[PDB]
Length: 215
Image: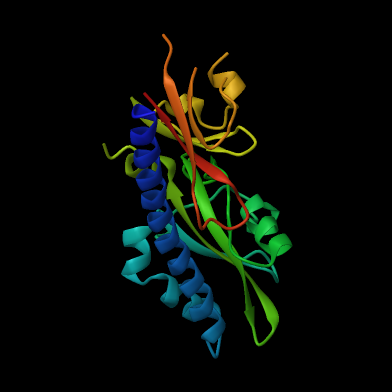
């Protein structure tokens, strides 16, 4: 009843921290879309100029626009993509269009670097016509560091998919795969035997994700 209160308080503060951090990144991606919709002439040079702002490289691994007309892909900071890369075939693109709003993706593998990332993406229209999908992505280790700024903490979806974990190998495993498992219910429960607490992250669009604390 006491160590339960204490884990409940740390889980709450841990969730509201990752919430604030992710929300700030969301806002920047929202503002990137509004900036691009505001271009009077949205040609390649103007799009690239908007993407080259240092605030984007300081706060994302990269930001980018996948264009609807022919798959033109502008990414800053720029590095190479695979031969025949077409952003329109990728989940961060197709899911932004299907949801018609900002989404936050589960982890995937960056097509250029092989790193594990997640993206925030949303459609960009100009005068009501689709320009493409704008996104920023961030490395999972960056997020995992935020989560574990102080036993340990990981991040897991409502369905049981591990999203962030100090053991990087456990990322994208199910909880049943990681612990051959506790049931995801908000609160604290005994499960070497350990305490494990689930706290929802508020404010995230389209997902229910939990901070898991292990003590």
